[PDB]
Image (cartoon, rainbow over all chains, first blue to last red; front, side):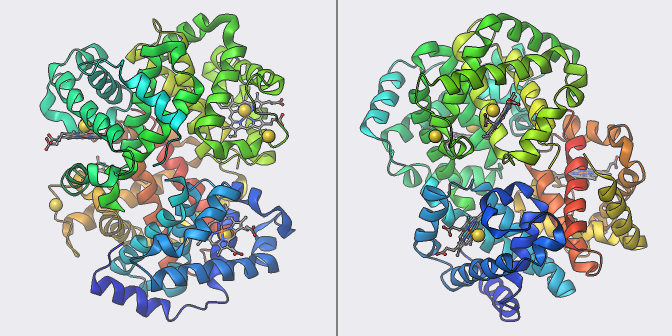
Length: 146
Length: 146
Length: 140
Length: 140
Ligand code: HEM
Ligand code: HEM
Ligand code: HEM
Ligand code: HEM
Ligand SMILES: [S]
Ligand SMILES: [S]
Ligand SMILES: [S]
Ligand SMILES: [S]
Ligand SMILES: [S]
Ligand SMILES: [S]
């Protein structure tokens, strides 16, 4: 996907301020709470019976850290997302069979987490740039379905 | 997209029996009837007030003929759908701003029309092959959003 | 909102389905499993091969649920309440998948009822299956 | 189905929105127009530039509709009946677009209410906006 230099600037400046140890777990936890059918894929994570149990679950925080690292890798390779996410696409598509609509959902939850964390700093133009990114990541993760 | 030789065989044998002057208008008409918000894009077509008016509308039949020709062109270039639909993608995305979910809808309506026309000949394996095709066409038409 | 004409159309088309309802439900399931392979992960304990007795038996259950919905079209949330609990709470079915099964049910009806599957009836059946799907996903 | 806890959560969060409701509706609209440019074709007679008085005035109408839905959360189809007629019949809004505006409304709430936008309240607000969207698309 193609961001303008101003879009790249907006995305890069905000991402350098993200707590990479926490935001991934926050987005994954909210995905499991808001879209409860995604809990089907995380049976081995233990207690997901309540929102507090989800957000306090150490396996959720740990796995969210890996998810955020993949988004960081996408941000560094904005015009080769397909090659970047190739092995991840085979995992999610060929072995896990996650419906790709859920890639869009997780991306939109990440956008909600960034808005929550950054407040008025997460301006409409900054959001518009992040929507391009999360859409490109979702599309690249789904290429093995395409 | 990649069809197996058996999938290609199933698709090609059925498509050679399609009435290319009628099936496109039938799918477009049913799209306008079943998903009425798509009528927003066809104000210049005249009377679309009732299902009979839609299916009997000569502009609907005429335009459906062009849509079916584009599907035929996709069937002939199954591994360069992106290049095949490039100018069509710019038209629908950059100038018309059709939401790409509607490309999937039209593809699924075409599948319904083929099932109606061919009956038991439209077996589950034949359908599965056509779903791969219409998904690939929809994805290629949406590339200018991607 | 199913209109009066929609309810008449759905009653008529499903009434013509008759005692084939079980077979058509099984065919719609096979269509879904072959066309949309992600749906197969919900049935790991099924044999999904053609002619499977488990798919045939399940297709009859699906058809009977739709018949119940038709017979109680004005009161579908109540009629399908136990089914919505099952799909959302226990099975945690992805809502995307109801669109896939609904499409395969329409394809199955189109392939078997050439006279009934007019554009108007097609529209009514799509609205009906969307209404059933809305009820079955209402309980996450 | 909005649970009792969902209704409490939605009442609380929207109650804290207070007299900013109009401004937040306008911001959600701007977010949608910039993030999802296809939505702009529904407003060709609007000036969609930042600070537009038409967007500000429309955002107040949107906020007032949601406030009406909150105040009549048990009877939303009736309260929003005229609005559902408008969007489906006259404007013929693509149902996909309600998901886009709902997402931008959540983003707007998240950006302005850091204390209220907990995971539980996030879930309740998403279900609420999905319920509003279902009503507004029920009339095609
Ligand atoms: C933007 C979307 C997503 C990204 C970037 C992402 C990223 C990742 C990463 C980096 C891993 C670890 C792979 C490894 O250990 O080598 C992973 C694993 C996994 N993901 Fe995701 N993911 C996404 C969406 C989803 C969604 C929506 C679901 C379920 C609803 C899901 C389910 C899983 C599961 C079950 C695993 C564990 C697989 C295993 O350990 O074998 N993913 N994902
Ligand atoms: C698989 C999906 C589709 C295919 C293959 C397709 C194909 C075509 C073709 C071949 C044309 C004629 C272009 C020309 O004259 O050079 C066209 C035009 C058009 N299509 Fe589609 N179409 C698709 C989906 C849609 C949908 C879903 C809508 C609206 C809901 C739509 C709206 C239009 C409009 C308004 C035009 C006229 C544009 C103009 O004349 O400037 N298309 N399409
Ligand atoms: C029109 C839509 C649907 C209808 C009417 C329907 C109906 C039913 C019925 C009647 C049962 C059996 C209930 C019982 O035996 O207690 C059932 C079970 C089940 N359904 Fe559905 N269903 C629908 C959609 C789906 C979809 C889209 C999926 C997943 C892709 C799904 C997955 C399942 C599963 C996994 C079971 C349990 C089967 C077993 O373990 O024996 N259903 N459904
Ligand atoms: C939560 C979702 C929504 C709510 C609560 C809502 C509410 C409203 C309200 C209250 C009005 C004014 C009614 C009147 O003045 O009589 C309106 C008008 C309108 N809405 Fe929405 N709406 C929603 C979603 C959408 C979406 C997704 C679109 C398109 C992307 C859309 C497009 C329009 C348009 C084009 C108008 C007419 C504006 C004008 O010509 O002045 N709405 N809506
Ligand atoms: S994940
Ligand atoms: S078209
Ligand atoms: S299976
Ligand atoms: S099912
Ligand atoms: S505009
Ligand atoms: S709106």
